Length: 164
Length: 161
Ligand SMILES: CCCC(=O)CC(=O)N[C@H]1CCOC1=O
Ligand SMILES: CCCC(=O)CC(=O)N[C@H]1CCOC1=O
Image (cartoon, rainbow over all chains, first blue to last red; front, side):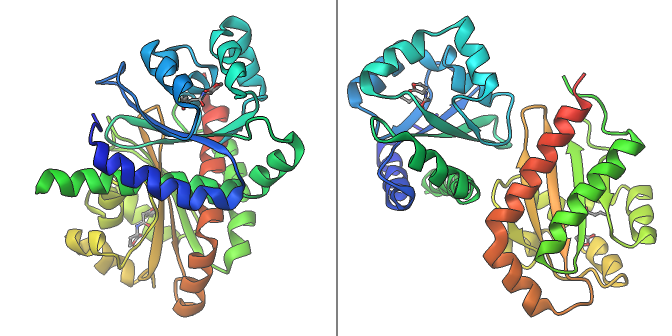
């Protein structure tokens, strides 16, 4: 269920420390399990009103990047054909995200053996587009590993907390 | 929905795809092993391991008792075969038999997909120098993980129904 505010604070802490090495960016680490679909865990520096609105309306159920990630193992851009396709069918999430300047970005995806899907979603925000996309592309293997090691760390911390 | 990964022409093309890329990290032994976690009896194996070892491993379903496969099942991050999680599993029959093929030192990279598959990329220096090998894997582990991801992504697209 991943409700432990204290572990999630160390995870957010672990991500922010390492993710700033690829630039000053917005990120969201979002973890969902099929057994608790309306309570995804979100660990992010996105604007809080957007996060709250996203949680309150269960927007992960209609979010083109999350719907695409279900079918992926490899990272993808939000202007990839698969996301554009889903956007044409339901555009609500991107239309509302535009207010908070969440427009262009990338999603990294991970499935585990506990029925979780984990995503690391990254956006520049309002900043200039080209240098961001080119930094993400040159560093995509490293960012994938950060998602992998964040998720391992998270599962590890929840494992120790449950033992004690 | 995904089909069984059993077209010989496709698997040989994917073998060439892996082999050309993984040789950037040294002269090494590799096995790409994909296993369905619901029905795990008959995994797909694309490998340059010694053919007699591969044949023996398939005939005896050794993945079911292989410490690195049993470890990968509960992992998302790569691990060395001397890591504490693997030594715990070490039934040691698989490693004892593998030693006769110089397959002693190695790493496993793992990937769970959304079709109940677990894909692993297992790599070993065989009889070549273990120090150079370990250093090359340690500094290239992010690229090797991405090689597994892109290989599996290709397989998923090729076998999609
Ligand atoms: C609030 C966290 C939302 C996510 O973690 C997924 C995500 O980043 N979706 C993007 C797509 C466009 O607007 C978003 O928020
Ligand atoms: C024949 C392919 C076997 C594998 O793909 C898994 C693997 O590499 N297991 C290692 C562990 C020690 O001996 C092995 O063969």
